[PDB]
Image (tube, each protein chain N blue to C red):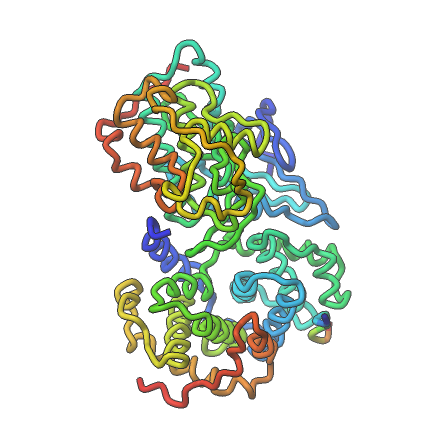
Length: 10
Length: 258
Length: 297
């Protein structure tokens, strides 16, 4: 229950 | 629904070619890399398990991304937006209950706004000229399964697993069409669990022999061999659950006999 | 944009906005314009639309309605369709006392099934065939239309949206609560529509799930495990249902000669695996003598 995430420099 | 097996298969074989994205497309994109693509798809995989979407939606989404990044140069900050927006699209196309947009904002951890997602939605739509009904590695596998003597969830599962593995690796698999990648997978997945092989009624239906598959087949095997050692594992963890019969733990062959 | 269209009357209103008769000021072409209301912060482009377009875009056939242009204007969407005179439910209301010439029936249905067989072979389910949704023209063509609820299926099929087909044309496998369905459901509907063309009044007009089953039952006979292996195991099946028996079709459908009856029932099969299909139907003996007579409007 934990997939949100910011992949790169924005 | 055998009434239109072939009629569909044929249509599909012809649609991929249309909805095929440009091979070294990443090579002209000045600020992104095949590497960051994977971090991107790898995530979507992860988004797909959380929100309880269908494998289809992954494959759809990946392909909208590939197609779109085949024409619009996008910067680092934005790759995630493009990919969120396509997930959304594959959702609206394929799920009975698409996740909502705020839920899609949430998984980017509030990076982009609502507007932004929705605004890209469109662009993706415009750029894709609304042609969202793509064949997928999934579609074909699904069909090929039907020639299964006899059916076996493991083989089915591994087949998927593999197939999905290729979403992540822009090089080579951007080389291959889904029908082949699906050919490459189903066999691989067979021989492994049952030491059988590409059944002859699919030579007949798809006209792809062992040989013709090889070059996909070789790559697909590496990719399988080195799967416990790849930078992105979200698929691998996925095919650890009982859902998929624990297939990612199966240990692949060590030589393809091809 | 629409700078180039003039709205004429409002023909029809549906789903997400309206539907207008429109003429193209440069070319004269009379078109139908379905506006689709968007709005940022809402769900974006709604998915009837997404499906409506992508699927329609790939369906090119004399008897499928033709999308011309989709006009993306930031704030709304407009689907540009060729215009067609009227839907099949007016034409039928308009001949309640006249009737429909057998060879117009015979023909309309040929056409219909031609459209559907292209649909199916192109892995699209229509999922809402009914008269309001089939459009005809002066010249005696007829085209599947309103793809609002269409979707791309797979092989084999997955579980889809169960809330489906207008009560009256809803095949039983859907009624009796099924987890899987397919093309067959498109053919229940023509099936019905067929008959509706023959008698100029609805085959099975129900006003809830139960009634619509019952009416079906009192016509094709309560079904059992011999005419449709699996029935008594489908989720919403009740042992209590009554066991009516079959009427002879010469009651159901009195003008239909020998060969229509035949197809009508192969269309109206209980067992979906067995219920006839398109391209199959087309080759049926009903249709050996087909032509293209022009409708009296």
